[PDB]
Image 1 (tube, protein in one colour):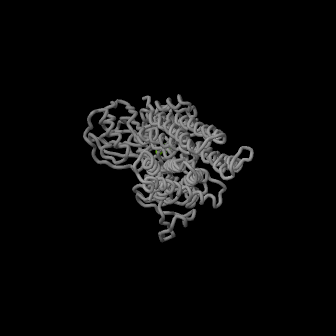
Image 2 (image 1 turned 135 degrees about the horizontal axis):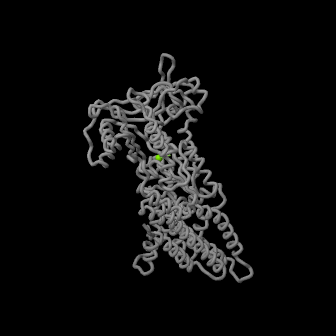
Image 3 (image 1 turned 45 degrees about the vertical axis):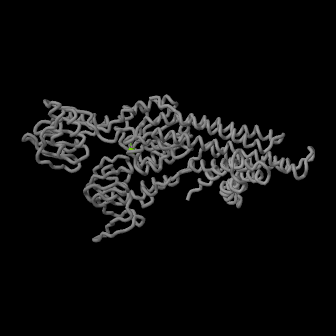
Length: 638
Ligand code: ALF
Ligand SMILES: [Mg+2]
């Protein structure tokens, strides 16, 4: 059941019922009865909407279009009524195709958090709903479960994925507090090995977590609420037309009906100037305008779709050109989304190949996500992989150990060599690793036996086309540029430098992104382009929200107004460009579609009929539609 077929039947009936009687061999009950159907199908839907708004609201333009059909029907030139009814039904169907907004992400957002939780009660562990969790409760989050509440760890250690909140799927090691009575009072002193969030996914170990916020006051409950209260962005052209009808419809139907009904000064029959007022009124129904505005929208959206970007409506399509600022998530948006091997720093008498081969020999046995990067990139650099190690063992939260060439190998964080039996870390290599950590490198130190072979550094590299699209967007007038990421500030600064963004903010929560976005939106229109769950509120409050189409979360795709479906950034200088020209195509098509009405309707009070109205109105409608179709031609300029 879809209502577009009534406009199609009015098209078939107008055309074939204009053809059957005239320049045709068809009877007047079959050939002209089609024109009878052309009044019924297109008129009956606009009629019921007219009734719906005339119950309470003041006026509707459908009154003007429908009575413009009806007066031509009860008078001469019924092709005028059928034509106006057909083209206005079609312009209504085109606005309905431009009006499609699913705007629902609550279904995906509700899945991030569980409904129930295990809570400790002395010698028992009860099951309660999360809305019945009290602050100070100890919930038991066991293996690979979704965390049900914000708080801090009091028992157990585990590697937790905080992707829905930090945007980083890189697991973070979590340890219990030293003193929980102290930790509940001093929430500002919670180290990131301790702060846990609802919606995170637990790792291998169970965690007792003391609750901090209530069920609705958690960070993820806040991002749900913030997304739900999004302002539905309205296109500047459409609300302009709403206010314009609010003035134009009653003004014209008052000034050109009863003031033109049976005017005493010029000779008229009391029954025949009754036709004279409706000539002006019926032709005053500005149908060129009702068809110009949605056709440009649909053409621009179709060109964007063949260009590889989804646009959910005309309002973001119009907003993309007017932007002054744009903000970028890092991981998955400006970066590829995976750590590569980017720095090798040998030490002492160790070669580069010894360091890389011992690293790949151990990381072939590990299952941490960095092991796979190390193995594939040592295989890239050396062409080969050495023989794998023996006696793999984990030092939990710090790294790994193995045995290569009858010597004991330790790899991991700087805290590992502070914790195990062998030779301690020299200060110079310590400082080198410190320098790598500050430069945004996740850093592993490698010892083989008595000797430190050295250190190695991995990083999520930016996309190759990032710096290019950044410079292009600066050329197109976007001098307000920033990075806003949940990753730490070293990686944010290093990627922002490597891409060419001047201001980079890391360590941000989703609300902090919303804060930065509102601060930019105060000075102009702003776009938030990202790919994660924690970017969805900043997308929702921005002037236009854009999601990375392929790698992105379903939450961010359902929330965003623009989708970069090729998952590449080179679609952004194209998009804004199209948006600018689209406004030109509607602006021209606005004034024309208005002007000719304002040009043909005073001319209708001074000697014009209903017969020529189709000829002017079609001449006003088709041409503007034709200009909108120029939007189907545009260039990439690669
Ligand atoms: F991927 Al992000 F902040 F969520 F850089
Ligand atoms: Mg992300």
